[PDB]
Image (spheres, coloured by chain):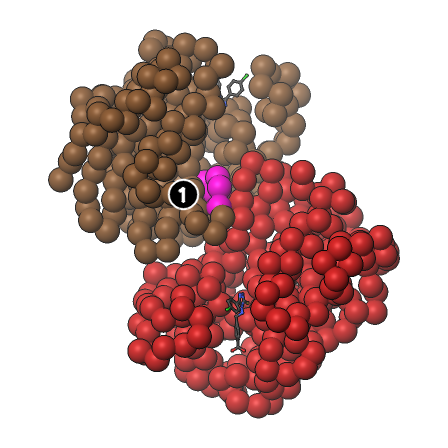
Chain colours: A brown, B red
């Protein structure tokens, strides 16, 4: 069912980096990774949590639809793209933490906890501030657990409405062309060691879907582009994309 | 409406001619290289797969975007048609026989009513129920395409929200960190003049630009110019990098 391919480590070491890529072939129900141990080690989800947070916010009516505007609170933050109005599409795209922190406060800890249990999401533990636990609280999730969660979303099998799931998958749109469609979410965990970067999602082909989840050590923001670059090198090696 | 004839340079570069029509949604302003051709109505050809999909989904002819429509075993000229398809791939490869079967299940009565509800083109389905958008009486202009697409974008067509969301998913053509294009190609060859279509929209962070283009297309060799010329216009207008 699972196969370890250490040759993928060549894509990590050439960028003076360390991490894991996990792939799941949906048609064949087979998994592949460069590092079986790390594939199953759990980390703070950081902004990959915007996928379940979006789902919950939509299903509860906290977010009406993908056009609703969440106005900037006027607090100038370090990431420039955060300092303006957003909707669900752009808030996901730019990983706009303050928008989702407000979602979390409106959702509340009771409903948040209940929903993550229903989602079977990670360790299901929201200990910490209700509006930052995915950044510095108790929640943890592994790459293989990310894939399990994403497979449910792809198939509309999560316990929220079909509409909520369709809207979040639209908001996850990252890249598309005549060869493939990538729906995904980046993450960057900086508050608690070890600092790591994430990229989780899937690649839609004409006749199959490949789920993926990667994380890597990220001591500085300098290497954030490596999340997508290394994943795409693995996808290219495995002939999933040209 | 504003006419910018300088866009014609993008057509003459390839010894071609046609029209691109743009609509700036935020500003409610339109732009085109040729106001008269912008309003000239043609057979929609495979751009008709947008309303046809909507109707098929809303009536349950298509259950969802995963349902598989098996190849009937007839070897047709376009190789990608000779295989099983779902709604996503049928739209991607403009697989006429899949949609012809849809049209038959839908029937002329329901098709006619729906196109009237959609205010679509001249709303005329005269001809074969399974080919009228290729060689029948239906006609639509580039500006009329944009009117229809704007309703779809806003989920304002008289079909369910789910049907409209699914079709907009199936229209996905290109996406990156700068833009998202949802669109549908068309190639009208059965009746003169032979023309190529590309209609859809460009999603930006803070605006949407609707577009509809058609161009003379005497041979299939120039089909790539539909997208290429459109993107040159988009580049000139600073809509995409
Ligand atoms: O701990 C936080 O509050 C936090 C920090 C950075 C981010 C976003 N990181 N990030 C970035 C990012 C990070 C830093 C800079 Cl300067 C630019 C982009 N790109 N993609 C992602 S994900 C999210 C949350
Ligand atoms: O009149 C028809 O039955 C008909 C002919 C060609 C098409 C497909 N046109 N087309 C094509 C196309 C046309 C010819 C070839 Cl060889 C390959 C693709 N690319 N994109 C589009 S749209 C659709 C319908
Ligand atoms: Cl989409």
Give the image location of residue B106, x and y in percent: 45, 81
Report whether the residue tagged 1 is closer than 8 Å to ligand 2. Answer: no
Judged by its main secondary structure, the magenta piece is strand
Q: Give the residue at x 49% y 67%.
A: B94
Residue at image coords 25%, 47%:
A26
Q: Residue A188, relative to residue A71: is it above or below?
A: above
Element type where label 1 sits in the image: loop
Q: Quadrant of residue A76?
A: top right
Q: Quadrant of the N terminus of chain B?
A: bottom right
In the figure, B137 relative to B231: above or below? below
Magenta stretch bounds: A171-176
User: The C terminus of chain B lies in which quarter of the figure?
Assistant: top right
Is B64 contained in the magenta span? Answer: no
The residue pinned by badge 1 equals A242
- Residue A27, given in percent of the width and then of the height, sits at 23, 51
Lateral position of residue A13 relative to residue A100, left or right: left
Specify whether B194 is left or right of A103: right
Local crowd size for mark 1, using a 10 Å CA cut-off: few (<14), some (14–19), many (≥20): few
Q: Residue most toward the left?
A: A1
Based on the displayed image, in which of its 4 quarters is residue A197 positioned? top left
Q: Residue at x 82, y 63 (%)?
A: B34
């Amino acid at each position: 069912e699972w196969q370890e391919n250490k040759s993928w480590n060549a894509h990590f070491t050439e960028h003076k980096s360390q991490g894991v890529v996990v792939l799941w072939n949906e048609n064949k129900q087979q998994g592949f990774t460069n590092n079986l141990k790390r594939a199953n080690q759990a980390f703070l989800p950081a902004s990959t949590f915007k996928i379940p947070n979006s789902l919950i916010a939509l299903d509860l009516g906290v977010v009406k639809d993908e056009h609703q505007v969440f106005k900037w609170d006027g607090q100038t933050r370090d990431i420039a793209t955060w300092n303006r109005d957003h909707n669900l599409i752009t808030a996901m795209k730019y990983s706009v933490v303050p928008v989702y922190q407000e979602f979390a406060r409106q959702i509340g800890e009771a409903r948040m906890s209940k929903m993550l249990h229903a989602f079977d999401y990670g360790n299901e533990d929201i200990s910490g501030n209700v509006d930052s636990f995915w950044l510095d609280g108790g929640i943890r999730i592994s790459a293989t657990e990310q894939i399990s969660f994403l497979r449910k979303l792809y198939h509309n099998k999560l316990h929220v409405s079909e509409r909520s799931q369709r809207i979040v998958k639209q908001a996850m749109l990252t890249e598309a062309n005549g060869d493939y469609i990538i729906r995904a979410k980046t993450g960057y965990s900086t508050r608690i060691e070890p600092k790591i970067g994430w990229w989780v999602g899937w690649v839609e082909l004409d006749d199959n879907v490949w789920f993926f989840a990667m994380n890597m050590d990220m001591p500085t923001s300098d290497g954030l582009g490596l999340r997508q670059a290394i994943t795409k090198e693995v996808l290219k090696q495995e002939k999933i994309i040209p």
